[PDB]
Image (cartoon, coloured by chain):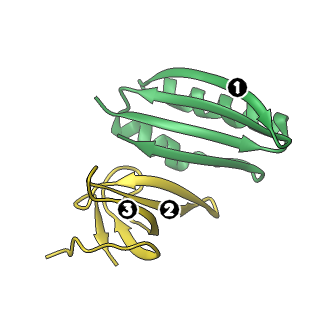
Amino acid sequence: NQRIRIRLKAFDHRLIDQATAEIVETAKRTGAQVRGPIPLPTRSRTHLRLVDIVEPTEKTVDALMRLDLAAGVDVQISLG
Amino acid sequence: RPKTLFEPGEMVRVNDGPFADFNGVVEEVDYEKSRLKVSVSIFGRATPVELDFSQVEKA
């Protein structure tokens, strides 16, 4: 019944969409499910995305840790 | 015998979930919700995540 919640921010939309795609792929190859991702309105020239991972497994968490996210994208992540 | 006394700016230790084996500081604390707001320096960037007192150890 826990969820991984992720918020992405970037000044470069190309980087944010690539990071979002990478997170989605990592989750799905992991046996987990994705909710979203969704874009939020851009604020102060900052692009914003939200994505959640439901039914995460240990393999999901490990795959997310291994994933190298590009310079220039901020990722806030929680599990609960 | 981990201590449950945590305060803003205090460093903590994570030993559960993918954030296990990582340290960070608790910028915000929530005794009512029993959750600590600590971020982990991952990829060279802080990753503010909520961890339980037992999920992390006092540093």
- Category of crowding for the residue at label 2, using alpha-carbon neighbours closer than 10 angstroms: few (below 14), some (14–19), many (at least 20): many
A31 w.r.t. B36: above or below: above
Q: Are marks 1 and 2 in contact (CB under 8 Å)?
A: no
Place of residue A49 in the rendered image (x, y in percent of width and height, measured from the top left): 67, 32
The reply to the same-chain question for discs 3 and 1 is: no
Element under label 2?
strand
Disc 3/disc 2 C-alpha distance (Å): 15 Å
Element under label 3?
strand
The residue indicated by pointer 3 is B29
Disc 3/disc 1 C-alpha distance (Å): 29 Å
Colour given to chain B in the rendered image:
yellow
**Side of A55 relative to A23 (left or right):** left
Farthest residue in the front direction? B32
**The C terminus of chain B lies in which quarter of the figure?**
bottom left
The residue indicated by pointer 1 is A39
Q: Does residue A30 show up?
A: no
Disc 1/disc 2 C-alpha distance (Å): 25 Å
Residue sitting at 42 percent across and 25 percent down? Answer: A32
Residue sitting at 50 percent across and 49 percent down? Answer: A65
